[PDB]
Image (cartoon, helix red, strand yellow):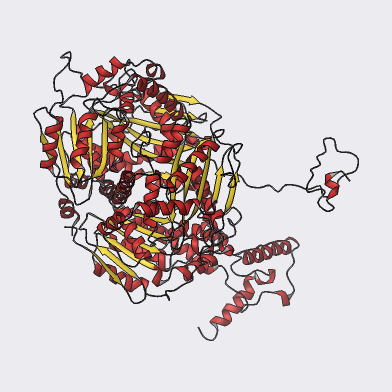
């Protein structure tokens, strides 16, 4: 069987629209377990720096009780069937998802009926979640990777709603009140911004009947009739450097502005990342990895680990690399990393393009294994693209990438650009911004 | 090839003159990356024997002396200890080069 | 018969420890010297647990299973 | 449309099980009974080095060729190990996975184990042990299994600090020639047919005896280990002997595990239907986490209580959990609690077999343990046959046994085994 018709044998996601504008999408497979979730366009980018932690505080409180099921009884409704109830919030998308069995498919929709509609916010829960979130961020600032990524968003998107963290500053956490959470729920938990996704052993018609009978009362109507626009954000080439020499080793991330979701050359950028890839100190290949950055990083013992990311948002994003290493090699890692980017702008040959295409194909198919990743892709794709892209379309878009358009796209996005730098730890040998800006181009080109 | 080529090989082995410093053939090989890797892959006994023979040769060439004729390394008793390791290193380098070609 | 170290005949210097702040005229026999040993590898700062919500799920319930890979990070799952 | 998994037992003892998914991607694993169970004191840490040294040169493929050819087609090579068995896995596209098996079989069948490469990755052993011991649950379970057994299961997953630099390639050759035999292997395929798997088994796999070396029966020891290391939280595992895999009481012990609480079903929840969490929550007012530990092996099992607590509150947390189990063992439980525990257990099994990794791991585990693959519906059916009286018998089995204790942290107020 050829890969194309094997990819065509995957069942298609079925999408339908209620009269509220809420989208309902399902994908059917042969599993005995299903994953049902609600995806809302309500992140930290929709906040106005006085409700900067409203989404995090709400997603803390969302499993603490409704106006019909008071508190822990809701927990029993999840725990007496073995379902796993989960939630997360990015800067743009907020998901409440749950994994259960198929026989419990109606009743569990009931939970997603009243999690996003009839949340009850008791005040004792408000101060309890207030100091829980305070010690949660006091725990989370120890993780240097989250600190570096939040610093990168702070220095890359200065003065924009996309710089602020999902959790927000500590002063708002001690300042969010009941009415502000009510206003956030009224403005952002509306009907046309919500996608009910299901993956696994579900049928689309039964899911539609349950979705109608439960979520037909979601608002669709505005409070003050003022549409919250999702404005463009100004990327700013800059640096931020937090020097703390007591830390054992440093985390450094360098990014440039990338296109987002709607631009198809994102797929080309993914192949570029698949040329450079990732490396960790606990790998197995050694010096014989195909990535030249990883091979030189294990040959000279430069870094503890590095990875490449392509983070996207509405018409914007970040595209770059993040490495943790000891201090004495930091600039050398930068030099080698920058050199790899310049090769992808100048000397891209078909062998590494074929290798990166194969890596992206295998990673893309193997990522969509499991009802929870399939439901995540359905909800995120209908929030971002407005439709679910079948994997055959992804295969057709991948197959059109050769070396010429790869180095064209990489010269567009990487060559002679102003990056955003975020360093944390013993970063004295991290070079000054003029050295990185000089490393963004070659004099031999 | 039968009659005198082996005899000419014996005469050339006597004439080249590393046998009268106690050296074997593979001690005389100039280091490259391949030869250094093949030396690095040697076991401890052959490595220590090689390094002692090399510094004995340097001691003898300091004083402009040679070994006594009974201590000259014999042509038949000369073992080619290094060249399987060197051939394996050359083979894997050629594999890496032909992969880098395509 | 006091002097608990001298209660044990051969186990006098094992039960006791005798540092010398100012070393006198006579040197002790077996001066002793540490070998230049190795160093442990460096690791990043870990995740502390300061609340009940973060600690949930951290208690082990299944046997320890380790996994290595050629280009995937090494992991351990409980 | 996922038609039927086909099963085959060759006369040399080799197992081949494959399923025709017609998937875009294929996953092929080889399951060998070659864990840390099969080392005596002479060759400790050999299995760890072999797990790390799977990607070395082979008699038929070099390590440059193996690494570059696996990364050239985008496939994945992984080794997953426990105390009992090891598993080798390749993941790829259907059009390439055939030659991927070639690489896998070299790694299993003809390793050269050159001395310089083994000397190279002993440092990788040290780094991997440090990374895996960065979590405290690892060293708690390692010390717990060391204390709980005398021989053949007290051997660690991770190599001891003295054996690093002391493992040679001859010991790895001995381990391969004595435990990678024919009748200790199951070859599992997903996204393939039977004919290609039978062909590659006929090519590479059909040369060794099959019985190999047995082991040392895992005699129970008991006792306690207390490691004072100065952290903010104190970890303590108290276990006792329990039934093995394939016994009629392993299902009752798993039901008792999920009845006492084995994981949070709600993110940032309060663990309402967990009995141990209920008792310690009504007791204490500090951060904690208590759960039930189950670990069943081929001929033995351990069941017990895992507690993470504060330094000055460890005694009341441990005593509250232990008195909760003592109250369970007297028969103070409801039938709806056992029904919810069975729901939790069968839900965990069904969501464990959903991905291809978990599915192929379960097929390989079933083939190595019983030699006869059973459908998930049969597993749920024998889960449904557990009565609450067998759960009370399992709890009384835990209470009236010789406990093994492993603790780490500030042990100022952590109790002992006789004090419980």
Quadrant in which the C terminus of chain A is drawn: top left
Q: Is residue B87 visible?
A: yes
Q: Quadrant of residue A188?
A: top left
Report the front residue among D115 and B88.
Answer: D115
Report the front residue among D173 and D354.
Answer: D354
Where residue D123 appears, as percent x and y from the top left, is: 54, 52
Where residue C26 appears, as percent x and y from the top left, is: 90, 43
Q: Is residue B89 above or below residue D224?
A: below
Where residue D396 appears, as percent x and y from the top left, is: 46, 52
Q: Quadrant of residue A254?
A: top left
Q: Quadrant of residue A233?
A: top left
Report the front residue among A273 and A198.
Answer: A198
Q: Residue at x 66, y 47 (%)?
A: C37
User: Farthest residue toward the top?
Assistant: A224
Q: Residue at x 52, y 56 (%)?
A: B33
User: Farthest residue toward the right?
Assistant: C25
Q: How many marks?
A: 0
Q: Is residue A347 visible?
A: no
Where residue D383 appears, as percent x and y from the top left, is: 31, 55
Q: Is A33 displayed left or right of D168 in the figure?
A: left
Quadrant in which the N terminus of chain A is drawn: bottom left
């Amino acid at each position: 069987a050829t890969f194309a018709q094997a990819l065509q044998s995957v069942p298609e996601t079925q999408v339908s629209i209620l009269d509220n504008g809420l989208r309902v999408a399902s994908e059917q497979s042969s599993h005995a377990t299903c994953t049902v979730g609600v995806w809302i366009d309500a992140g930290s980018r929709y906040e106005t720096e006085k409700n900067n932690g409203a989404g995090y505080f709400l997603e803390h409180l969302a499993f603490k009780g409704t106006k019909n099921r008071p508190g822990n009884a809701l927990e029993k409704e999840v725990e007496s069937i073995g379902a796993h109830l989960n939630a997360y919030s990015t800067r743009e998308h907020t998901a409440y998802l749950i994994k259960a069995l198929s026989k419990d498919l109606p009743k569990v929709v009931e939970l997603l009926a009243d999690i996003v509609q009839n949340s009850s916010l008791e005040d004792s829960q408000i101060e309890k979640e207030r100091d829980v979130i305070l010690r949660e961020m006091q725990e989370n600032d120890a993780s240097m990777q989250n600190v570096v990524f939040d610093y990168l968003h702070a220095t890359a998107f200065q003065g924009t709603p996309l710089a602020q963290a999902v959790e927000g500053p500590s002063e708002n956490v001690r300042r969010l009140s009941r009415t502000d959470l009510t206003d956030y729920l009224n403005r952002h938990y509306k009907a046309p911004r919500m996608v009910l996704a299901a993956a696994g052993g579900v049928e689309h018609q039964q899911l539609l009947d349950l979705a109608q009978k439960h979520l037909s009362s979601v608002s669709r109507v505005y409070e003050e009739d003022a549409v919250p626009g999702l404005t463009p954000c100004r990327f700013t080439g800059s640096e931020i450097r937090h020097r703390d020499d007591a830390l054992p080793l440093a985390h450094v991330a360098i990014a440039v502005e990338g296109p987002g979701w709607a631009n198809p050359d994102n797929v080309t950028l993914q192949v570029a990342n698949a040329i450079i890839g990732h490396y960790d100190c606990t790998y197995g290949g050694g010096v014989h990895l195909s990535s030249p950055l990883a091979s030189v990083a294990v040959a000279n013992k430069l870094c503890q680990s590095f990875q490449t990311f392509n983070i996207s948002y509405s018409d914007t994003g970040l595209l770059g690399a993040h490495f943790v290493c000891d201090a004495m090699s930091i600039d050398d890692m930068v030099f080698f990393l920058q050199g790899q980017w310049m090769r992808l702008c100048t000397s891209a040959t078909e062998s590494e393009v074929t290798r990166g295409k194969n890596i992206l194909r295998n990673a893309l198919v193997s990522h969509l294994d499991g009802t929870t990743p399939v439901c995540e892709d359905i909800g995120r794709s209908l929030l971002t693209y407005g439709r679910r892209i079948p994997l055959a379309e992804w295969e057709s878009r991948i197959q059109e990438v050769d070396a010429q358009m790869l180095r064209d796209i990489c010269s567009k996005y990487f060559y002679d650009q102003c990056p955003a730098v975020a360093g944390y730890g013993p970063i004295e040998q991290l070079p000054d911004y003029n050295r990185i800006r000089s490393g963004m181009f070659w004099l031999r080109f | 090839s039968s009659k005198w080529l082996d005899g000419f090989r014996k005469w050339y082995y006597n004439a080249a003159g590393f046998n009268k410093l106690g050296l074997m053939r593979d001690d005389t090989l100039h280091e490259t990356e391949d030869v250094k890797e093949a030396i690095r892959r040697l076991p401890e006994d052959l490595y220590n024997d090689r390094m002692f023979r090399i510094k004995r040769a340097l001691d003898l060439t300091m004083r402009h002396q040679i070994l006594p004729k009974d201590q000259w390394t014999k042509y038949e008793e000369d073992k080619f200890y290094l060249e399987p390791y060197l051939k394996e290193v050359i083979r894997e380098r050629k594999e890496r080069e032909e992969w880098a070609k395509k | 018969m006091l002097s608990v170290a001298a209660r044990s005949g051969p186990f006098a210097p094992v039960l006791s420890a005798t540092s010398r702040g100012v070393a006198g005229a006579l040197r002790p026999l077996l001066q002793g010297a540490v070998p230049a040993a190795s160093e442990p590898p460096v690791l990043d700062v870990k995740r502390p647990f300061l609340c009940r919500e973060s600690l949930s799920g951290q208690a082990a319930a299944r046997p320890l299973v380790a996994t290595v890979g050629l280009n995937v990070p090494a992991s351990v799952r409980f | 449309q996922p038609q039927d998994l086909e099963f085959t037992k060759l006369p040399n003892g080799l197992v081949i099980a494959s399923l025709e998914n017609y998937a875009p991607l294929s996953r092929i694993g080889l399951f060998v009974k070659a864990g840390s169970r099969y080392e005596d004191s002479n060759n400790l840490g050999t299995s760890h080095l072999l797990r790390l040294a799977s990607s070395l040169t082979t008699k038929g493929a070099s390590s440059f060729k193996i690494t570059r050819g696996i990364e050239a087609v985008g496939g994945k090579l992984s080794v997953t190990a426990t105390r009992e068995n090891m598993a080798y896995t390749v993941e790829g596209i259907r059009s390439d996975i055939e030659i991927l098996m070639e690489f896998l079989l070299n790694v299993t069948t003809a390793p050269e184990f050159r001395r310089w490469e083994v000397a190279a990755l002993r440092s990788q052993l040290k780094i991997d042990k440090a990374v895996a011991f960065q979590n405290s649950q690892t060293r708690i379970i390692e010390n717990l299994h060391d204390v709980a057994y005398k021989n053949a299961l007290a051997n660690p997953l991770y190599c001891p600090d003295y054996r690093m630099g002391k493992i040679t390639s001859e010991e790895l050759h001995y381990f391969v020639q004595n435990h990678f035999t024919s009748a200790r292997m199951a070859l599992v395929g997903l996204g393939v047919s039977h004919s290609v798997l039978k062909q590659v088994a006929e090519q590479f796999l059909n040369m060794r005896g099959g019985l190999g070396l047995a082991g040392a029966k895992a005699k129970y020891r008991g006792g306690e280990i207390r490691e004072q290391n100065g952290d903010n939280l104190v970890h303590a595992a108290i276990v006792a002997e329990s039934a093995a895999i394939g016994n009629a009481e392993a299902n009752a012990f798993s039901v008792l595990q999920h009845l006492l609480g084995a994981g949070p079903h709600i993110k940032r929840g309060n663990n309402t239907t967990s009995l141990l969490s209920q008792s310690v929550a009504k007791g204490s007012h500090q951060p904690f986490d208590v759960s039930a530990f189950n670990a069943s092996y081929s001929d033995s099992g351990l069941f017990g209580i895992y507690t993470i607590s504060q330094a000055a509150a460890a005694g009341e947390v441990i005593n509250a959990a232990y008195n909760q189990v003592k109250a369970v063992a007297q028969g103070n439980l409801s039938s709806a609690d056992v029904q919810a525990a069975k729901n939790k257990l069968k839900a965990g099994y069904l969501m464990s077999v959903e991905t291809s990794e978990g599915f192929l791991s379960e097929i390989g585990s079933q083939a190595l343990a019983a030699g006869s693959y059973m459908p998930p519906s049969t597993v749920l059916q024998q889960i449904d046959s557990v009565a609450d009286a067998d759960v009370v018998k399992a709890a009384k089995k835990f209470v009236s046994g010789k406990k093994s204790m492993a603790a780490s942290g500030n042990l100022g107020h952590t109790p002992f085994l006789d004090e419980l």
